[PDB]
Length: 139
Image (cartoon, rainbow, N blue to C red; front, side, top):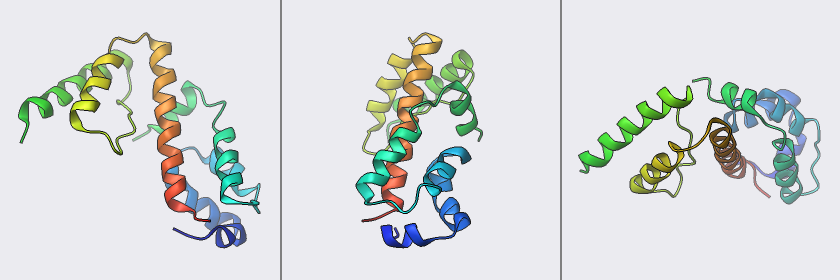
């Protein structure tokens, strides 16, 4: 985790490289790098949210480029069923969630229409990206 003043002072490439693990969408990081120096971490995070506002199915697919056995098996079967039905890997923000919680989300999302699921997967992607950004850059 690097300070905001440090991040604001980095070369385009070093800044871009720092942001790369947040999400596999080069255009998003590029946008943030080009808007330095940020007034505050608050302003950086707000700008980051605005930069992901127009993400669609194309950005979803690009981003996704690569004890209790009942539960483990249920998650495996659900994931196979998800991938078969929707044509992509199942994306959920996993941090803070239990296995049972994930299974219940998976089960509910297996009942979605294509567009409903694109929307939620993207909403989860946005959460994941922000969490990673928040872990990477400080105040």
